[PDB]
Amino acid sequence: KVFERCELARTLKRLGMDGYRGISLANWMCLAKWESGYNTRATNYNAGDRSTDYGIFQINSRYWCNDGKTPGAVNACHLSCSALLQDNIADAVACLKRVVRDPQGIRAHVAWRNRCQNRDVRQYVQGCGV
């Protein structure tokens, strides 16, 4: 499913993401956008390390989830990658909360670093009532 802007702003915030580890809702919304276009079914296969990025946040199968088909898997989220492909993002959000608790925080997502970090991201939450 593809979330509309404010729809995602409200569910992410309902899941207590607004200010999680200092990361604002707007900044979470900017990650989602540049990562998958707000699409939960988004998946990106990297023939390189043979890993795959899953769901709305494009979490990689090599360190966070297990899809049973990528070398050197750690599965730090103790979750199946297939859970990151559901209409309900509770599972993906909880795993993301885990990703950012790591030293690098949100700077883990290079898409967010390129398109979000240090920039104005208040349009992502504009008029959403959040």
Image (tube, rainbow, N blue to C red):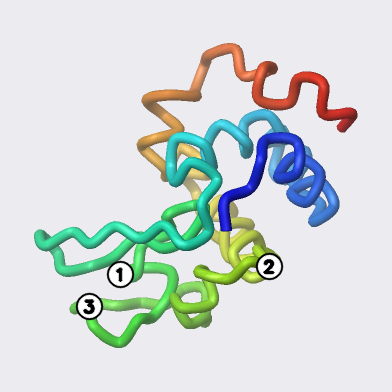
- Residue 94 sits above or below residue 9 on the image: below
Sort mark 2 into few (<14), some (14-19) or many (20+) by Cα contacts within 10 Å: few
Q: Residue at x 62, y 31 (%)?
A: 27
What is the secondary structure assignment of the residue under circle 2? Answer: loop
Image location of residue 3, percent across then percent down: 63, 47
Q: Quadrant of the C terminus?
A: top right
| Kind of residue at disc 2 | Asn
Q: Nearer the viewer, residue 73 or 30?
A: 30
| Kind of residue at disc 1 | Arg
User: Of tags 3 and 2, which is closer to the observer?
Assistant: 2
Question: Which residue corresponds to mark 2?
Answer: 88
Q: Marks 2 and 1, how far apart in space?
A: 22 Å
Q: Which residue of the protein is positioned furthest toward the bottom in this rendering?
A: 68
Q: Are marks 2 and 1 in contact (CB under 8 Å)?
A: no
Question: Which residue corresponds to mark 1?
Answer: 62
Q: Residue at x 16, y 69 (%)?
A: 50
Question: Which residue corresponds to mark 3?
Answer: 70
Image location of residue 104, percent across then percent down: 46, 44
Give the quarter of the image for residue 115: top left
Is 49 left, or right, of 89 in this rendering? left
Q: Nearer the viewer, residue 69 or 109?
A: 69
| Kind of residue at disc 3 | Thr
Give the quarter of the image for residue 72: bottom left
